Figure 1 (cartoon, rainbow over the protein chains, first blue to last red):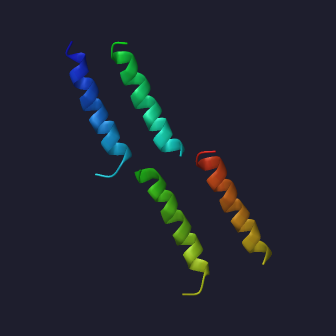
Figure 2 (cartoon, each protein chain N blue to C red):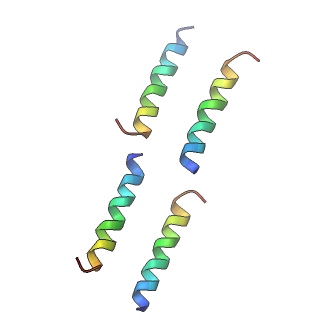
Figure 3 (cartoon, each protein chain N blue to C red):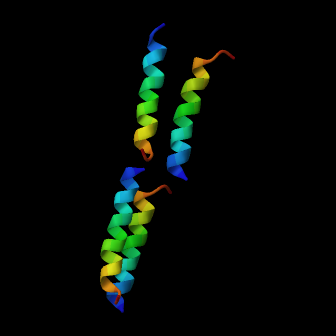
Amino acid sequence: MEFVAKLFKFFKDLLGKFLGN
Amino acid sequence: MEFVAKLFKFFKDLLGKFLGN
Amino acid sequence: MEFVAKLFKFFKDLLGKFLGN
Amino acid sequence: MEFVAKLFKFFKDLLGKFLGN
């Protein structure tokens, strides 16, 4: 379903937050 | 190192259950 | 991460202070 | 002198309890 679209978008945010840039 | 291991443990374990086996 | 970068600010701010420049 | 060892030890405890064991 469309849930998976949010998940990666959520991860991209978290991963970028935990690192630089 | 904790932080890399912790982040990996989150990413791998979550996505692994997502995918078929 | 950004968070441990705060820690490194902690060490030089203190440790460098003592030692003669 | 003594204060140096105390502060150092303290830093070691900080790095231990704070960062990954």
